[PDB]
């Protein structure tokens, strides 16, 4: 926190030393003294994180400024004298109180970097064409309803970020900005995209999440540099056929929360380089046979909350998959071919209609997380003993009456979620779960026993048993809750000497 006199002391130091950078940031300055006009040797002025509500016209004397950093102040305007900054390359105005781009900024035609994030800007003037050297323009988190056609005169634009505004369309002249590689349009109101979009042959990241798009232009097939395309939460029900076949480096695609009833049509060429595929919250009724036969590096597929009633014949060929989310479908069984997924670390199957699991589940030797909550499981296969990497197993609200004795081979298991089942007892093999930390048993109205070997679980720090009768245990013990129950199992069981 600097007083006026301290700020003066710092300007006088900087001009004395003929320094080219003056940093007065993070100082709670309310006013910048006029004396800064003497610092004509300055090429960089940092004034960010202060309490400035106005910038003195004297700053326009800093004829050699290349960088002016003004973020996190309360500026609502800039002096016209900033005309004189003929070399200003970068201007940073985010987190201020601008209701507009100050009109002088449109005369700083040497700018290549303009940051206006988090303001209240409502307009971008036709004059934006004066700034033909801009390569990075960021106006996200403002109140822009429209981009002018003059935006197409920024042929050096590399990064255009207009996230979190109110755009309903884009000017077709945006297609003249053929150098754009990062275009973020998330959280607007976009009703469509112009067909000139395919001109952007260097575009590699296109963010369209949270808009009102109902269709994609077939021209998007020509953005062959695309590496990541996010269309989450629009109203898209189909893609032009073989659009994705044309996207030869696409590696991350999100179609979540749209209107799809099928996969995009066009054969396995669509997903050959795909690494992450997010299609949750649609009505996709099947995974086509063959779509991932070329997807050498597919490793995250999210199909949560669709209309899957089974899995395709070639499902076990997805041998590089790491995370597979199939929750909130209508699956009635998992095919024995699940055993092919030797890379699988995360399997999410919650809230389907499963009564049993396949034997092949035991071949998933890398599986770390298995989420089976809200099914109808009536038993666990004995092959679960071979899930040697299993660390989290969630079974909340199934129909289990017991566990397989093989469950005690799961020595990496830290979290066992058994709440809301029909358990009558746990196996004595519970006791070799060396790393068990969390055991949830709440709401098992038929569980009248706990095995003594639960005392052998030396890392057990969390247990719930609310609404379990436990009537083979002394009433006042189980009334005391988990601390007394575990204490009773350790001191009054056969392992008293080794725990
Ligand atoms: O939120 C994030 O993790 C990135 N931001 C983002 C993450 C996912 C998004 O889906 C959208 O629809 N928009 C998104 C933005 C982040 C974080 C910190 C700094 C910069 C960031 O990224 C800038 C950016 C990203 C993209 C893009 C579009 C689609 C997929 C992936 C990246 C385009 C232009 C820019 Cl300038
Ligand atoms: K939607």
Image: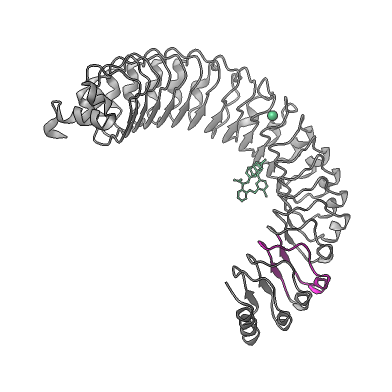
Q: How many marks?
A: 0
250 up-or-down from 471: above or below: below
Viewed as shown, does residue 172 lie left or right of 473? right
Residue 439 or residue 54, whichever sits in front: 54
Q: Position of residue 293 (x, y in %)?
A: 57, 26
276 up-or-down from 349: above or below: below
Name which residue lies at 78% across and 40% down.
198
Classify residue 385 by image quadrant.
top left
Q: Quadrant of ligand 1?
A: top right
Q: Position of residue 26 (x, y in %)?
A: 59, 68
Viewed as shown, does residue 368 lie left or right of 317? left
Residue 178 or residue 6, whichever sits in front: 6
Q: Position of residue 119 (x, y in %)?
A: 73, 54
Name which residue lies at 69% across and 53% down.
118
Viewed as shown, does residue 323 lie left or right of 171? left
Q: Could you tell me if residue 344 is visible in this image?
A: no
Q: Which residues are magenta?
A: 65-93
Name the main secondary structure of what is drawn in magenta.
Answer: loop
Farthest residue, direction bottom: 16
| Quadrant assignment for the N terminus | bottom right
Q: What's the image's color scheme? A: one colour
Classify residue 115 by image quadrant.
bottom right
Q: Position of residue 107 (x, y in %)?
A: 84, 65
Name which residue lies at 77% across and 59% down.
134
Classify residue 19 by image quadrant.
bottom right
Q: Is residue 77 magenta?
A: yes
| Quadrant assignment for the C terminus | top left
Q: Could you tell me if residue 295 is visible in this image?
A: yes
Residue 106 or residue 469, whichever sits in front: 469
Residue 397 or residue 305, whichever sits in front: 397
């Amino acid at each position: 926190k600097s007083s006026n006199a301290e700020v003066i002391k710092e300007l006088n130091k900087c001009r004395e030393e003929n320094s080219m950078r003056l940093d007065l940031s993070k100082r709670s300055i309310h006013i910048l003294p006029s004396s800064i006009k003497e610092l004509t040797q300055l090429t960089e002025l940092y004034l960010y994180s202060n309490k400035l509500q106005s910038l003195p016209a004297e700053v326009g004397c800093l004829v050699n400024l290349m960088t002016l950093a003004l973020s996190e102040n309360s500026l609502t305007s800039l002096p016209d004298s900033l005309d004189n900054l003929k070399k200003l390359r970068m201007l940073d105005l985010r987190h201020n109180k601008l209701r507009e781009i100050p009109s002088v900024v449109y005369r700083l035609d040497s700018l290549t970097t303009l940051y206006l994030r988090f303001n209240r800007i409502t307009t971008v003037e036709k004059d934006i064409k004066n700034l033909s050297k801009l390569s990075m323009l960021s106006i996200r988190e403002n109140k822009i309803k429209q981009l002018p056609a003059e935006i197409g005169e920024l042929c050096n634009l590399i990064t255009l970020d207009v996230a979190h505004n109110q755009l309903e369309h884009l000017p077709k002249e945006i297609g003249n900005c053929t150098q754009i590689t990062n275009l973020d349009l998330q959280h607007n109101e976009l009703l469509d995209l112009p067909d000139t979009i395919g001109n952007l042959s260097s575009l590699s990241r296109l963010g369209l999440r949270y808009n009102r798009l109902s269709a994609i232009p077939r021209s998007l097939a020509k953005c062959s540099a695309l590496e990541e395309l996010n269309l989450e939460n629009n109203n898209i029900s189909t893609l032009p056929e073989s659009l994705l076949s044309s996207l030869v480096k696409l590696n991350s695609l999100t179609l979540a929360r749209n209107c799809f009833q099928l996969y995009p049509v066009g054969g396995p060429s669509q997903f050959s380089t795909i690494y992450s595929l997010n299609m949750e919250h649609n009505r996709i009724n099947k995974i086509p046979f063959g779509i991932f036969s070329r997807a050498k590096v597919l490793s995250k597929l999210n199909m949560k909350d669709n209309q899957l009633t089974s899995l395709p014949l070639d499902f076990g060929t997805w041998t590089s998959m790491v995370e597979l989310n199939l929750a909130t479908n209508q699956l009635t069984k998992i095919p024995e071919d699940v055993s092919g997924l030797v890379s699988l670390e995360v399997l999410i199957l919650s809230n389907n209609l499963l009564k049993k699991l396949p034997h092949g589940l035991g071949n998933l030797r890398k599986l770390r997380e298995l989420d089976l909550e809200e099914n109808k499981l009536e038993s666990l296969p004995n092959e679960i003993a071979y899930l040697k990497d299993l660390q989290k197993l969630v079974l909340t609200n199934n129909q289990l009456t017991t566990l397989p004795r093989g469950i005690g081979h799961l020595t990496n298991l830290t979290h066992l979620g058994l709440g809301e089942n029909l358990l009558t007892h746990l196996p004595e093999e519970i006791g070799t779960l060396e790393n068990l930390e969390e055991l949830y048993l709440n709401d098992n109205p038929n569980l009248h026993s706990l095995p003594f070997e639960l005392a052998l679980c030396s890392k057990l720090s969390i247990m719930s048993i609310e609404n379990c009768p436990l009537s083979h245990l002394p009433p006042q013990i189980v009334a005391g809750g988990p601390s007394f129950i575990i204490q009773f199992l350790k001191m009054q069981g056969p392992y008293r000497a080794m725990v």
